[PDB]
Image (tube, rainbow, N blue to C red; front, side, top):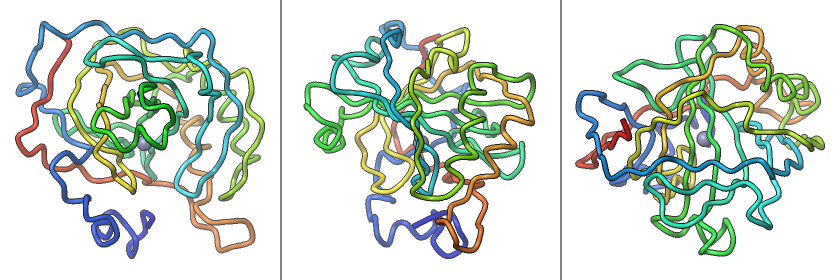
Length: 255
Ligand SMILES: [Zn+2]
């Protein structure tokens, strides 16, 4: 599985039948169809005590991992019930500024998309959570090309060290609060992971307001390799999946 012509998203179903399930992600968010739900509570992002450990290239993206042995970085409120712990955050981008996001807004595609992954602590470990319908909460943030995101530079600068698959590097004292937009207005629907196993255990929280990054920032992302060290170089670009059918599900808005 990958994003190539032969192992791309159109092929995942072979291996992962759930690929053509009822609550697959990503999706196109029709803003005219989204339902304003007044019963929706404000998001509660507590990341002041966040502990980042490292960054690694897993061959499909680069993940910044956090210490989730305690309620240090959590997400609550909104459409959620109980506390969700931050375990990792990563991105999805394109070969061009014209594509890269997972989710689309009225068919519009962004440069990239940030996923902050949290797991329902009632289930004890990530592993068990991914086996429940209310197992995960993923915070989705759109990235547009414009002005630099100061808070993102610490990450861009470390990319050289994890160019190939299986590389990792210590990445302590990184504050995720620097990647958040000003407003926390969101869209929410019941979905799945956007990559295999594509388990349907995610509660998506898509922020309305995108953050901007400079052309130079996103460009460094495109210098990554899907391949392992000493193998033919395959640039890590377009690690996104085509939008899926909403199939009855309803997209709710907090605004
Ligand atoms: Zn993702």
